[PDB]
Length: 114
Image 1 (tube, helix red, strand yellow):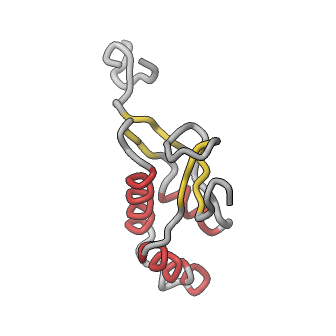
Image 2: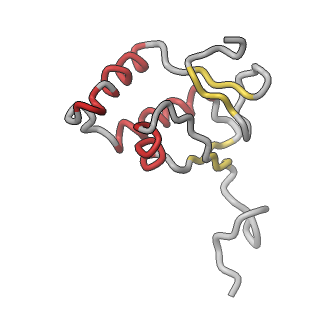
């Protein structure tokens, strides 16, 4: 009995030294079902910075949805993806302005003040 993968505090009871996030910014219905399917859950250690989160997020989505240029409707996603990887991506901050990962983080290409 008991199990071996419980949640809440480890071993007899815990989870990985990482935090599981489920908040994904949906720009449109497209990256809604697509982003959710490719990324419905993520594990972030307490050392991962928005930069790393964005990196793994972009890589994950790119890995799952590689054949995007094939779909004309989604196509554009390729141009935007390339542009995002070019330099300007999407900044993310908490409900304050400080660049930190928390339960409620605002991910977008718009500064805190915007």
